[PDB]
Image (cartoon, coloured by chain):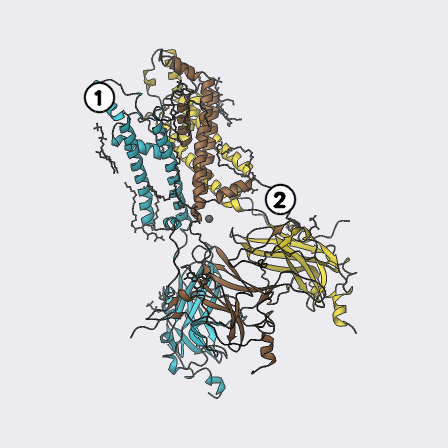
Chain colours: A brown, B yellow, C cyan
Amino acid sequence: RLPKARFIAKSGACNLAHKNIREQGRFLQDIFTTLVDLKWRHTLVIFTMSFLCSWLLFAIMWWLVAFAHGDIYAYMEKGITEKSGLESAVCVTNVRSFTSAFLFSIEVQVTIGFGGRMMTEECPLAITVLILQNIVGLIINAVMLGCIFMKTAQAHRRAETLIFSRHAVIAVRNGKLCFMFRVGDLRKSMIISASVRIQVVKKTTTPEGEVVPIHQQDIPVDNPIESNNIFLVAPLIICHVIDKRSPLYDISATDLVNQDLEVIVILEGVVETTGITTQARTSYIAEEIQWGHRFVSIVTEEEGVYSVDYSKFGNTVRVAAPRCSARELDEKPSI
Amino acid sequence: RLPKARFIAKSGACNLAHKNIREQGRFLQDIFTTLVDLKWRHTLVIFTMSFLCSWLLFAIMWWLVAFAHGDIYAYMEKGITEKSGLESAVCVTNVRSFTSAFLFSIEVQVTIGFGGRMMTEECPLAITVLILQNIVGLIINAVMLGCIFMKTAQAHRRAETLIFSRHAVIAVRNGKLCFMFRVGDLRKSMIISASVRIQVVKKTTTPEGEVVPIHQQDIPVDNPIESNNIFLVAPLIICHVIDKRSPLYDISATDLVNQDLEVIVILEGVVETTGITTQARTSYIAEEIQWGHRFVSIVTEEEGVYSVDYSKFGNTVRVAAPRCSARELDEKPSI
Amino acid sequence: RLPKARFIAKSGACNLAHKNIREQGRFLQDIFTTLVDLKWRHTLVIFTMSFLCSWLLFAIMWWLVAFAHGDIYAYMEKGITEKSGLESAVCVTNVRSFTSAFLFSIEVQVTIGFGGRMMTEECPLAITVLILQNIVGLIINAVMLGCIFMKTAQAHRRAETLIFSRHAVIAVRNGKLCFMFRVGDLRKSMIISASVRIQVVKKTTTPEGEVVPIHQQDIPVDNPIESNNIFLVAPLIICHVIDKRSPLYDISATDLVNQDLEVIVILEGVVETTGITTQARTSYIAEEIQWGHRFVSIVTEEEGVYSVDYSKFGNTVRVAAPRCSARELDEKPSI
Ligand SMILES: CCCCCCCCCCCCCCCCCC(=O)OC[C@H](COP(=O)(O)OC[C@H](N)C(=O)O)OC(=O)CCCCCCCCCCCCCCCCC
Ligand SMILES: CCCCCCCCCCCCCCCCCC(=O)OC[C@H](COP(=O)(O)OC[C@H](N)C(=O)O)OC(=O)CCCCCCCCCCCCCCCCC
Ligand SMILES: CCCCCCCCCCCCCCCCCC(=O)OC[C@H](COP(=O)(O)OC[C@H](N)C(=O)O)OC(=O)CCCCCCCCCCCCCCCCC
Ligand SMILES: Nc1ncnc2c1ncn2[C@@H]1O[C@H](COP(=O)(O)OP(=O)(O)OP(=O)(O)O)[C@@H](O)[C@H]1O
Ligand SMILES: Nc1ncnc2c1ncn2[C@@H]1O[C@H](COP(=O)(O)OP(=O)(O)OP(=O)(O)O)[C@@H](O)[C@H]1O
Ligand SMILES: Nc1ncnc2c1ncn2[C@@H]1O[C@H](COP(=O)(O)OP(=O)(O)OP(=O)(O)O)[C@@H](O)[C@H]1O
Ligand SMILES: [K+]
Ligand SMILES: [K+]
Ligand SMILES: [K+]
């Protein structure tokens, strides 16, 4: 049938819609913020076109300011007839075409300055254009260096190397029921101050009328000293003991076929080397909760040092377990 | 008359005045910190003016040293005479006017160095000025590039995108009279490790006369596992259960209007993308607190997906609730 | 025989061996990331080689374009003819060899532009090569500055500086057995917001048959207000008191030699100078726990100041202690 309403997909990225938000309006900072955060394949194109366009723009300007003053006419007539007169005190020496203007703009903008096409002092308009081009070039160059430095500072970024298990299992641990899943780390560095949270999403109904459509009740992670902190080195099993205070206290095996259950798992912490905090998410719906399974053991020391066999990360071995809601299991103990 | 003196405006900014603080003065570091943080409308202006003024200043120096050494007179006479006589070993070739001096300064500080106005081995004051100009140009260049790198790093920085409702409410949940409001977000990245702290700012009175005028009293947010943290994707209803420890345990509907209440809401977290901690604040006073109203349900399920209608963000309906102080209901629910 | 497998060695660096991981693809981003994090001995080499290779490559290009055109022939026949028959026909003036091509490439790419080898405006192919060289030089220059900027930024951080004692003790402190070790710091700065966590790695079996290879159990460190936060200026003695739920409850004094134990200590914090969160780890096994000892005092008052004496950091003196398991000292109280 048409897929259900899933609060967050199997890889985070909540499938929500945010409509009717008041339009704050398009800004001029959208362009810049996009420019700073681009892909290399397009950064190295805007970088090239910025130059290749500024050179051309100021080339057109120099070609004009050498057309108006009559410089092209001097270098076209006296260059044939008589070399004397210094070409009648042109604005810029030896600019006599559009290739000349283009090369002069390239020199003044890159700051090569060969010196064959030298700026004279015989017209202030040229001095104006030279000042303009120097300032424009400095600004463009500073901005492009900034972009490349930003791309360099974000070079260690990767995807989320935290992995989960597609199946979450309900089983019996230390006498009671337990909802459990597995989590594992692929990155070489050990995240610092890791933490886990678990939330059941439902549609609650208070006695007095309220109906919160997606109410995210929170669930306590099972742990000896009642904390959230975990030490992720080898893949490990996060558990939750379904007692009289958990919204799964009235969930049985037969009911777990059509059920308004969705368990959100949020794991976050600071990475040791890079130093930027990360958050990973996953979700399980009544399809991926299998009643009466358990996870296999993985670690084993073949010779000396231990070894984690990741080939069986999400495995699940069928086991024998009750078939009644956790409420029954204490309503009729010792059965 | 004047409204009762708030503590933090509903916008979020503090209103207190810090008067009579031993002055430390204004350092020189303020003039640089203010420079690294300017609007582009002014960053570009100072970027232009720094270079323009430096070029003009060192042009003045070059013109002066081309005067004092008797180099302008030699060029003017050689123009008056027939032959230049190698300008008789000038300080700096082909600098015969102020304009030429400006061009030479532009070439020396942008490092264009066309090379028609060279620099000779004659007078060492020229070499001293050249060293000064080189070092000053390098320092100014480095500073401007640093400021532009700062801008390109602060590209992502914006204002607060967190949203608190216009006015809180006080309703009945599970037979308990509790105070609740709504918080939401217009951002895109989930705030990593949010935390919601609530306080009551009220004038206390110790029995031994330790009167405090603005007393900040922490209040505990309702949570099934007793922690502040919240996962914020869709808009949430923050709530506070009024009980024996709650300062609001005496407030009635009719006595609400004439109360010196103020409830301060602080919300902290880390932005996943930009990685910089934030903080939002808001305040409620006895006018905003709507007694007896409760909010409306935003999220709706449709097209097999959830959807949030941000047009109803602040809507609140009136529902029939006890019109008596919390202590009245709690002491004698029916007696 | 072979040393028994460990979990975390005496210097952190978990000694596990993850295998069978579903290996991903190798991306060029890995090459760039390796480039951006390097050792100065290699940063300098890659920096130098980039520029040498680029100068040489474009020297080859310029020499080829001086060969294909009639340039080398013209400048070789001009010397014979003793007349400048090659002033304007040349693709790039005064480039008549490979050494001169190399000099011209250096001038164009470092932006010196001496001007003895000028860029003529005849051959369009040369103009194409010049534009290409300028763009490539700009890109390489920006990349290398970005690498140096990253080096400068992450320059401040250095290696670990937390000192842990070689082996622990099990004393009696305030009428109960306590497992103690000593942690000190050699750094000059302050670990802001430090924290201590203790775990027991051991192979556990459940009544239902779920066997966990290396289970990590959380140990409540002993603090008078039940918190982790430790303030570290003078070396501290971290202690844990063996109560009804500690896994070290039933381990006696005689059979501590052969017992599957391992105590992992993880100490986290935030340094003040650079604000880079750090985590330091260590582990103790059965062979390195000395029953009935206690650490000697280290700090003596010199009547002007206290004076820690780190020479005795790991010293530990033998004292009396009930030579029996922690269960017998309360189930058999008389002892
Ligand atoms: C000769 C000796 C020189 C030696 C230099 C060595 C020292 C420098 C270090 C090497 C780096 C050189 C600079 C390039 C840096 C980019 C390389 C690499 O890091 O990027 C990889 C790019 C593609 O990445 P992406 O699409 O953004 O992926 C998103 C992100 N990376 C992610 O996965 O999360 O993939 C690519 O980068 C593909 C590049 C193909 C095309 C390259 C040329 C483009 C520029 C062309 C400009 C010159 C010509 C233009 C004008 C011509 C006019 C005639
Ligand atoms: C010749 C080009 C041909 C070839 C094309 C080359 C392409 C160029 C690539 C690199 C561009 C370099 C400049 C980019 C500027 C982007 C900055 C812009 O997006 O910021 C917005 C500015 C004004 O916003 P703000 O509120 O004051 O500050 C932003 C604040 N942080 C905020 O978020 O809210 O909005 C503005 O943009 C300010 C406009 C009004 C400024 C008034 C006059 C400026 C002073 C004098 C001009 C100086 C010369 C400028 C040269 C620019 C050309 C490179
Ligand atoms: C007249 C001068 C006045 C101006 C001076 C003022 C300052 C401006 C210049 C600043 C100099 C640059 C700063 C360098 C900082 C020194 C860093 C130093 O640690 O590295 C020197 C190396 C040490 O190697 P390392 O252990 O890997 O270091 C990284 C460290 N482990 C880390 O924490 O990460 O030590 C070694 O172990 C030696 C091994 C080789 C290292 C160098 C190799 C040289 C290669 C090429 C260099 C020559 C360049 C020119 C070549 C031209 C070719 C024609
Ligand atoms: N569609 C929306 N888009 C963006 N922000 C919104 C939207 N709806 C409400 N808000 C935010 O909600 C806050 C107030 O919400 P509420 O609807 O309770 O206010 P109100 O009583 O309607 O008064 P106002 O006229 O300020 O909205 C404001 O700060 C506003 O920024
Ligand atoms: N060897 C591995 N390397 C990296 N990631 C893994 C590996 N094995 C499993 N995973 C991750 O664990 C999850 C397992 O879910 P999946 O849909 O792959 O079930 P599966 O293929 O039956 O698992 P398995 O084959 O490991 O039993 C996937 O998200 C995957 O990313
Ligand atoms: N005075 C000190 N200065 C610097 N580091 C020390 C000092 N004393 C001990 N350490 C560090 O503390 C660690 C634990 O040493 P401990 O005192 O427990 O045994 P030890 O007898 O010092 O062993 P070793 O002789 O190998 O250091 C050692 O690895 C050492 O690096
Ligand atoms: K940074
Ligand atoms: K230069
Ligand atoms: K030059």
User: Pointer 2 indicates a residue of which chain?
Assistant: A
Q: Is mark 2 within 8 Å of ligand 4?
A: yes
Q: Nearer the viewer, residue C163 or A315?
A: A315
Answer whether labels 2 and 1 touch (C-beta < 8 Å): no
| Residue A86 in view here | yes
Camera-nearest residue between B173 and B217: B173
Mark nearest the camera among 2 and 1 is: 2
Where is residue B333? Give x, y as percent.
Answer: 76, 71
Q: Position of residue A204 (x, y in %)?
A: 65, 64
Residue C79: assigned label:
1
Q: Which residue is mark 2?
A: A24
Q: Nearer the viewer, residue C218 or B216?
A: C218
Going by the numbered disc 1, the residue's amino acid type is Gly
Amino acid type at image mark 2: Gln
In the picture, residue C149 is in which quadrant?
A: top left
Looking at the picture, how far across and down is residue A281, in whole percent? 52, 59
